[PDB]
Image (cartoon, rainbow, N blue to C red; front, top):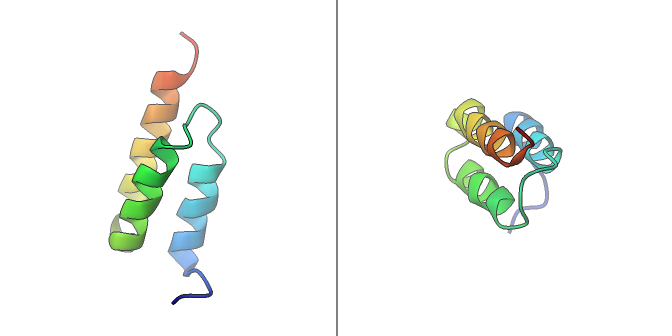
Length: 58
């Protein structure tokens, strides 16, 4: 039963929340996977960034 983040986790979690073209479903798909493997936070960010870029204008 956790109360608090970790220093790389909070960075990725804020950053994935900050993306506007991301869905209330998609967001959880990177965040949940971040709780699972925080060592790859950089690469989970790269997916959320890419999917926001897919759901942007042309």
